[PDB]
Length: 52
Length: 61
Image 1 (spheres, chains in turn purple, orange):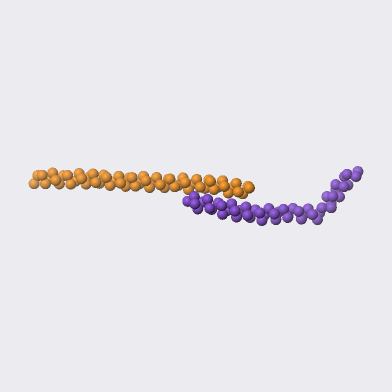
Image 2: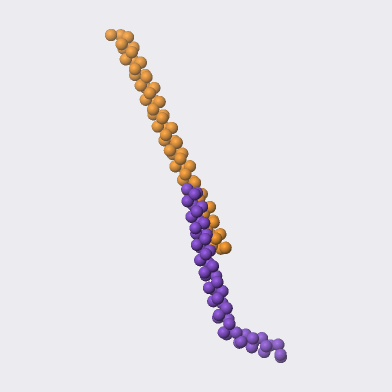
């Protein structure tokens, strides 16, 4: 019974994580791209507060 | 005739014994089966716990 229970979790604690890898990096890409176009606005906000 | 009585009296106790000794040979089989069930019902349950914990850990991770 253990023989078919230990190999159950391993075939899930691979699929589950392996799915997270697809989720994590796609959500890494999803935070960069939102930032990288609406970005100069940030640089602007900073500069405008250092040269006063 | 008497004596054949005495011999019809033994072959009677020596079924009483053989009836008593095969009404325990089940009792042993009952309590052994009612054991194994319970010796695998707790085991079934244990694997859930050891697996319910392992997959939650792997969700968080």
